[PDB]
Amino acid sequence: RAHSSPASLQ
Amino acid sequence: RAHSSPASLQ
Amino acid sequence: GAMGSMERASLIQKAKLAEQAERYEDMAAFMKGAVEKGEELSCEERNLLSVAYKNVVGGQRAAWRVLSSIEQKSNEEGSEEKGPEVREYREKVETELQGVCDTVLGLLDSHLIKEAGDAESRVFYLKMKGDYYRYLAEVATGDDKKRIIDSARSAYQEAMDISKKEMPPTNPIRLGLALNFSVFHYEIANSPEEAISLAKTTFDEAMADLHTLSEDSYKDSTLIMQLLRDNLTLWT
Amino acid sequence: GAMGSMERASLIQKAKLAEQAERYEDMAAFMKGAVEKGEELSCEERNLLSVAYKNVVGGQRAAWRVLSSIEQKSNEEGSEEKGPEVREYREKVETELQGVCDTVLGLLDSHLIKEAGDAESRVFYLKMKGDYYRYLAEVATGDDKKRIIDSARSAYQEAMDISKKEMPPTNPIRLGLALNFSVFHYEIANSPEEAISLAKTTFDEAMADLHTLSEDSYKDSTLIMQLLRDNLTLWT
Ligand SMILES: [Ca+2]
Ligand SMILES: [Ca+2]
Ligand SMILES: [Cl-]
Ligand SMILES: [Cl-]
Ligand SMILES: [Cl-]
Ligand SMILES: [Cl-]
Ligand SMILES: [Cl-]
Ligand SMILES: [Cl-]
Ligand SMILES: [Cl-]
Ligand SMILES: [Cl-]
Ligand SMILES: [Mg+2]
Ligand SMILES: [Mg+2]
Ligand SMILES: [Mg+2]
Ligand SMILES: [Mg+2]
Ligand SMILES: [Mg+2]
Ligand SMILES: [Mg+2]
Ligand SMILES: [Mg+2]
Ligand SMILES: [Mg+2]
C-alpha cells in the first residue's frame, strides 16, 4: 500500500 | 488508428 | 509440449487465473496447451484463447510501432548515423511478433478450423485467421506481402459469407468480424471506400435488428456498433 | 551469456530503445549483458539497470498479490475445494519472481558493489540490494524468512550510514533509500513506529536543505519528499 521510490534517481 | 474488435465476443 | 502433462481442465483454470493476474504470456501458453489436447473448444474457451493471444500480440504490435517510428526518423535527411542497432532491435521484435502469429495460425490449421462446424465456432476461428494474417501484413515488406494480404482477405471473406447466412446482423461475432474486415480494407488493402461502405452497411443492418434483443444482448451488440461508428467518424 | 557477442554500447542503446517500447524484459536482458562486460556503470546506466528490473519485478509482484489473494480466499471456511491449481500457479509466479531477485542480487555481488567506491554508486547499489531482498521477503514464509529480512535490513543500514556521511539530505538517492527503508520497517519488519520516525526525520532534514538547491534539483528532491508525506498520511 505504501509508496516506494521510483527506479531512476539522481 | 482505427478501432478493432475486442477479443471476447459472444 | 511443456503443457502435455497438465490436465485440460487445469490448463483452463490456470488460464483464467493468468487473466486475472494480467499474465497474458502465461495465459497463452495455458490455452495453447488446452488446444493441443485435441478436443474442440467451448465458447468460453475460444474467448480465453483469443484474449490471451490478442494481449500478447498487442504488446508486440505497440512495441513494433514505436521502434518502426524511430527507425523511420533515422532514415530522414540530416539524421545522424547511429549504426545497425535500431534496425536490429526492430527486427528482433518483428520476428517475435511473426512467431506469435505463426503459432496462432498453426493452432487454427491443426486442427481447430477443420473440426469447427457450427457457425459460431467456424466464424470466430476464420475471423482469428484473418486477424493474425492482418497482423503479419502490418509488418510485411517483402515478396510475400501480397500473398499475406490475400490470405487475410480470403479468411475474412469466408467468415463473412458464413456469418451472413447463419447469424443475425446483431451477433457480436458477426459484428466484430465486419469491424475487423473494414479495418483490413482501410489500413492494409488501400481500400478506404470499401472500409467505409462495409462499416455503414454493418451498422445499419444491426440497428434494424436491435428490437429483437434482450437488454443484455442489446448491450453486447451496441458496444461493437459503437466501434463501427467511431471508425466512421475517424474516416469521414 | 546470450549478450556476450554484443558491444557494450549497443546493449546500452538497445536498453534505451526497449524502455521507449515498454519492453522491460528485453531492457533487463540488455542491461544484464552490459553489467557482465565487467566495467563500472555510469549514473545513467545504473538508472537504466534499475528501471528495467523494477518494471520486470513489479509485474511479477502485482501478479503474485492477485494470486495470493485468490489462494487466501480459497482457504476460508465454506470455500469450495478446487484442487491444487491456484497454489501451483502462485508458486510458479513466485519462483520466477525469486529468480529475478536472485539475478539482480547476483549482479550486485559479481561485482558491482565491490567496485563501487563513490557514494552515489555505492549507496544506489546497496539500496538495490535492500530492495530485492525486500521483494524476496514479501513472499517468504519459511525457515530462512528471518535471514532474508536480516539481509534487507543490513543492506539498507549500510547504505544509510554512507548516505548520512557523504550526501546532502536532499540527495534523491538518499531520499529514495530512506523512503524504501521506511517501507521495509512498516511492511516487512513489523516496525510501524520506526517507519514513521524515519519518514518524518528524513522529510524534515530535506526541507531544511532545499534552500541550497537550483530549481531543477528542487523539483527532483521535492518529488521524493512528497512520497514520504503520502506514506505519512497513510500511516498516521
Ligand atoms: Ca468516395
Ligand atoms: Ca506510537
Ligand atoms: Cl505477460
Ligand atoms: Cl537486438
Ligand atoms: Cl482461408
Ligand atoms: Cl470525421
Ligand atoms: Cl516486457
Ligand atoms: Cl502452474
Ligand atoms: Cl549487506
Ligand atoms: Cl491519515
Ligand atoms: Mg485428462
Ligand atoms: Mg549531424
Ligand atoms: Mg550504434
Ligand atoms: Mg460485446
Ligand atoms: Mg567491445
Ligand atoms: Mg459448497
Ligand atoms: Mg482443479
Ligand atoms: Mg526525483
Image: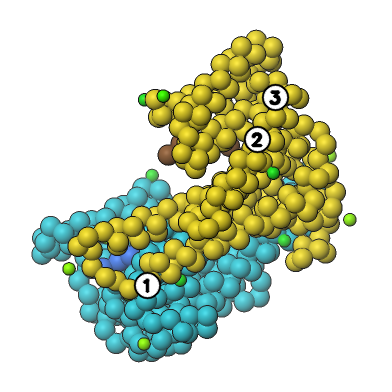
Chain colours: A brown, B blue, C cyan, D yellow
Same chain assignment for discs 3 and 2: yes
The answer to whether residue D70 is left or right of residue C90 is left
Residue identified by numbered label 1? D84
**Up-down relation of residue D19 to residue C23 (above or below):** above
Same chain assignment for discs 3 and 1: yes
Q: Chain of mark 2?
A: D
Residue D228 in picture, x, y percent from top left: 51, 26
Q: Work out whether mark 3 precedes mark 2 in sequence or the reverse, and give the earlier one.
A: 2
The answer to whether mark 3 is within 8 Å of ligand 9 is: no
Residue at 64% from the left image edge and 57% from the top image edge: D102
The answer to whether mark 2 is within 8 Å of ligand 9 is: no
Label 2 amino acid?
Gln
Q: Tell me the element at label 3.
A: helix
Residue identified by numbered label 3? D164
Which callout, 3 or 2, points to the residue nearer the camera? Answer: 2
Residue identified by numbered label 2? D157
Could you tell me if residue D198 is visible in this image?
Answer: yes
Residue D161 in picture, x, y percent from top left: 70, 29
Could you tell me if residue C70 is visible in this image?
Answer: no
Residue at 39% from the left image edge and 57% from the top image edge: D68
Q: Chain of mark 3?
A: D
- The quarter holding residue D116 reads top right
- Which quadrant does the C terminus of chain D fall into? top left
Measured Cα–Cα span from mark 1 to mark 2: 40 Å
Residue D114 in picture, x, y percent from top left: 81, 45
| Mark 1 residue crowding within 10 angstroms, few (<14) / some (14–19) / many (20+) | few
Q: Tell me the element at label 2.
A: helix
Pointer 3 with pointer 1, Cβ within 8 A:
no
